[PDB]
Image: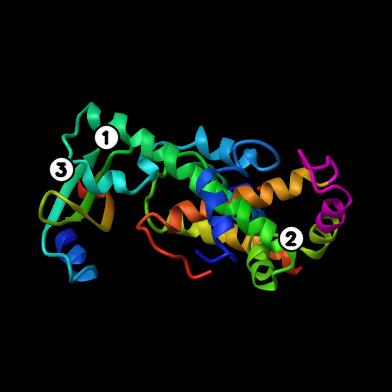
Amino acid sequence: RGMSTYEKTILLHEAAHAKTGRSIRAVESGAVSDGVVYEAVQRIKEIQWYVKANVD
Amino acid sequence: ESVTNFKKQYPQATTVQMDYDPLTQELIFQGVNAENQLGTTRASIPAADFR
Amino acid sequence: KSAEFGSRLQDVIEARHVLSGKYRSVLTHLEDNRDIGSLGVAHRYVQQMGQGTRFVNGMEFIRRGQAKLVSGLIADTVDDAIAGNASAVTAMERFGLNQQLLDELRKATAANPDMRKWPDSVRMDIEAVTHNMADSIVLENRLGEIPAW
């Protein structure tokens, strides 16, 4: 309650880093082959590779 | 609901098999063929929402 | 039979470019970082075959057979790209090559064709490029299919 409206939106913006908890699980064999997330990680890694040649 | 969705996604599947994965608390569906052979279709559902 | 390709297929079967020398990093990474569950064929037969030890004991043999073939294929298709085959270069770059690495690789290979190992200047880049490729093929090829690229 003792926070301005602007700050408490940055609080959610930084909480959007939840990916790290999920990027790790797809590097370790925690999310073995579960769809959706397993495919999203692969097609983010593909884009990561692409930018090097053309432009962890 | 889960069975209807699974059959809607994969019309070619004739039979369905169910299995439980204790390590991640997960329920798994998979299509099966004769001669105890298994297909390529698969699905996953957490136990919390089922309960 | 063709003299244009038979020699290279023989080398890929015999694993002569993979067991020692430049490219053994790929075989080391694949050998002791994956399990029988990665074959795909393991799932398709766990119930016809008697689900016992004779299944798991046998599947390791097939793992260690397949890893060498995959590594040999990668090793062949990298040297082909360095040779000049444009169609291979435009597929190599899918995993991160760029003119800077390729120019230096071509320069290095010309000075000394023996190359028991890569130079320290460019080791850590081409090494990572190959490892990215090795992972992708295992995922798309599970069913026994030819990926589009």
Q: Secondary structure at mark 1?
A: loop
Q: How is the image coloured?
A: rainbow
Disc 2 to disc 1, C-alpha distance: 49 Å
Q: Residue at 52% across / 55% down in the picture? A: C136
Tell me if residue C126 can be seen. Answer: yes
Amino acid type of the residue that numbered disc 2 sits on in the rendered structure? Ile
Q: Please tell me the numbered disc located at residue B22.
A: 1
Identify the subunit bearing mark 2: C
Where residue C15 sits, quadrant-wise, is top right
Q: Please tell me the numbered disc located at residue C48.
A: 3
Q: Earlier in the sequence, mark 2 or mark 3?
A: 3
Q: Position of residue B12 (x, y in %)?
A: 18, 70
Q: Is residue C40 left or right of residue C121?
A: left
Q: Please tell me the numbered disc located at residue C124.
A: none
Query: Would you name the residue on which mark 2 appears?
Result: C82
Queried whether the magenta region covers residue A21, the answer comes back as no
Q: Residue at 58% across / 64% down in the picture? A: C3
Queried whether the magenta region covers residue C107, the answer comes back as yes
Amino acid type of the residue that numbered disc 1 sits on in the rendered structure? Pro
Identify the subunit bearing mark 3: C
Q: Which residues are magenta?
A: C105-121
